[PDB]
Image (cartoon, grey):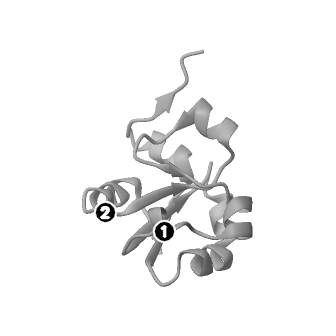
Amino acid sequence: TTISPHDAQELIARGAKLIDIRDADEYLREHIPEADLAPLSVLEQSGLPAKLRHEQIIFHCQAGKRTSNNADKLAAIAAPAEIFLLEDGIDGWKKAGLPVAVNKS
């Protein structure tokens, strides 16, 4: 259920939702352009909204830690989708040479 950045790309090309579970300030500083923001605490409170649902959902955070440690929560939050966790988070995505959007001041 953990997915490489390259394999996540292939899924996104087929309509998979990429969900960034970090906070807005983190997202605004640097994010994956395809990603939809939905902070974990919001998802825990009010659930995954219909607009972010799809047959395949990939979650990511900073370095893979928050996704790994909240795997069970995320499995329920996105049920009954096919659910994936991005290996090493946005840091992994960056290490793989894939594009990010960085705030210019």
Q: Is residue 94 left or right of residue 77?
A: left
Q: Nearer the viewer, mark 2 or mark 1?
A: 1
Residue at numbered disc 2: 11
The residue under the point 54% across, 66% down is 49
Figure quadrant of residue 68: bottom right
The residue under the point 62% across, 48% down is 62
Up/down of 95 relative to 63, above or below: above
Image quadrant occupied by the C terminus: top right
Element carrying mark 2: helix
Element carrying mark 1: helix
Q: Position of residue 95 (x, y in %)?
A: 47, 41
Q: Position of residue 57 (x, y in %)?
A: 44, 68
Q: Position of residue 18 (x, y in %)?
A: 45, 57
- Residue type pointed to by label 2: Leu
Q: Is residue 10 left or right of residue 80?
A: left
Q: Position of residue 43 (x, y in %)?
A: 66, 65
Residue at numbered disc 1: 50
Q: Residues within 10 Å of mark 1 (few under 14, many from 20)?
A: few
- Residue type pointed to by label 1: Ala
Q: Residues within 10 Å of mark 2 (few under 14, many from 20)?
A: some
Q: How far apart are the alpha carbons under marks 2 and 1?
A: 19 Å
Front-most of 48 and 20?
48
